[PDB]
Amino acid sequence: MTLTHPNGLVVERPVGFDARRSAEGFRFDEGGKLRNPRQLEVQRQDAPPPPDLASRRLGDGEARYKVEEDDGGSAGSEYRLWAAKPAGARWIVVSASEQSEDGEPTFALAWALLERARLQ
Amino acid sequence: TATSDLIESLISYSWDDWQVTRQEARRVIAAIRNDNVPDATIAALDKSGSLIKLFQRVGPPELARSLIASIAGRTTMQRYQARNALIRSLINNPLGTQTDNWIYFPTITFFDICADLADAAGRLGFAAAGATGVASQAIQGPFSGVGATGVNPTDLPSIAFGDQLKLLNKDPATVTKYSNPLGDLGAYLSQLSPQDKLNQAQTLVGQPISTLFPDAYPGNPPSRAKVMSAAARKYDLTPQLIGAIILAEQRDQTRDEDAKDYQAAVSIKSANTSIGLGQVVVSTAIKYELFTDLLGQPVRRGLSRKAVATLLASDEFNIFATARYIRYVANLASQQDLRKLPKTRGAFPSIDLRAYAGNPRNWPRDNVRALASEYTSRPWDDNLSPGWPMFVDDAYATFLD
Ligand SMILES: [Ca+2]
Ligand SMILES: [Cl-]
Ligand SMILES: [Zn+2]
Ligand SMILES: [Zn+2]
Ligand SMILES: [Zn+2]
Ligand SMILES: [Zn+2]
């Protein structure tokens, strides 16, 4: 269940998600044909994160992130996480989207993906 | 009039007798409702100087609501005389109708809602309609929300304390329990035969609206079918389209979700939940003025946010908002450039954007599929719901028969 990009990014595919390689990492789409599926993306990135983002300790280190909210539909507002952690002199970036009517999602799967990701 | 005479004595005080009784109050309301000349009656009560007294003396809020909704409903030329007398009665006696389910409506707003609603029902063609279907008795699982049961979300008990804490604690499992009941949409449809589906449709559409303003109607509240037909005519849709959208929402709805939906919205948090039959988002109803065709501008723009969430729990307001929103999504689509929506074009090859401007009778089925996606999610951002199109399309096929 491990995935390795030629650029060195290695990550764990989330259970029940279809995977696809992108230019700098991987895109994941929830399985089946859901009303409101989660989508995740993970990438090796050279450019540092923008300044003045929120932070949280993630596992052993920290991560910078922002959650953006937009009008959605009957399933709730659209939410999108953008998060980055330092990996060497570079960064690993995860974004993730989901609708919720109950406020901001936990984005648990997204954080787990970023947490275990490395540039080996 | 015969009626003004009866009411005057019903509400009169005598020496050592300064209390209108519940029974008298009920006879007044019944007399108002049975009146063939309601404007004349109000004119007569106002001439007597009895109109203010009428509002002052029908005391318990539940009876005050019936009184006020009935008078607001049936009057035309004398509407503003009754309105002025009510306002007078409310000086240093303010509580009025603003209790229980109606706590987010000032009394004069309650009057104005009923007047506007009654006028719209008359003008748009939904003032009356006998039931053609019967509510489900389900209390849990898919299709156990107000669409199936007729049980108003504002009438549901407070979520139980233990669950309230788990929800607040962002407990994943409890959140799911009060959230959409369905995961695998196709698996759910496979549980139902064609007749089962048609039966859900008849239950949904054939029962009376669950309304917060029953006395604003001349007799019994109309069936939802009658209201959907009126909304469809207003927004150049079809009732089959409106019904399909709502049946799909209501399949993916439970009684527990209704309780969370409404209670979160009027809690300290003022959550931006999706509410009622069409699962209309509170901020969306405000932003696109979704009550425009049932409520005049002054009444609409004065509603608090919690008052809007409450109206979305009233079936007729929800049906109209849903239809007005559907027509918005369609109009918006007709303004788009298909070349700029390649994912949408990919998923729905026969989509015809210009046709969205016209009646659904003339849309390709792919238009319905695409609008379904763009009803449950943000519309026309080229991000699609994988499951909703077929789910709504199935409901549509049933209604189309
Ligand atoms: Ca729902
Ligand atoms: Cl009259
Ligand atoms: Zn590279
Ligand atoms: Zn008496
Ligand atoms: Zn909900
Ligand atoms: Zn969309």
Image (tube, coloured by chain):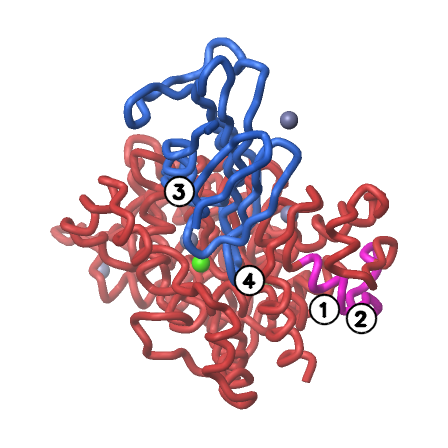
Chain colours: A blue, B red
Residue sitting nearer the eye, B68 or B195: B195
The residue marked by circle 3 belongs to what chain? A
Dot 4 and dot 3 residues touching (CB under 8 Å): no
The reply to whether the residue tagged 4 has its Cβ within 8 angstroms of ligand 6 is no
Dot 3 and dot 2 residues touching (CB under 8 Å): no
Residue B361 is labelled as 2
Residue named by callout 3: A109
Residue B295 position in % (x across, y down): 59, 47
Residue B263 position in % (x across, y down): 32, 47
Front disc: 3 or 2: 3
Are marks 1 and 4 in one subunit?
no
Write the start and end of the magenta stretch as one range. Answer: B356-371
* Residue type, numbered disc 4: Lys
Distance from Cα at disc 1 to Cα at disc 4: 27 Å
Residue named by callout 4: A33
Outermost residue, left side: B16
Dot 1 and dot 3 residues touching (CB under 8 Å): no
* Residue type, numbered disc 1: Thr
Residue sitting nearer the eye, A79 or B362: A79
Residue displayed at 35% across by 48% down = B102
Dot 2 and dot 1 residues touching (CB under 8 Å): yes
Residue B340 position in % (x across, y down): 81, 41
- Element at label 2: helix
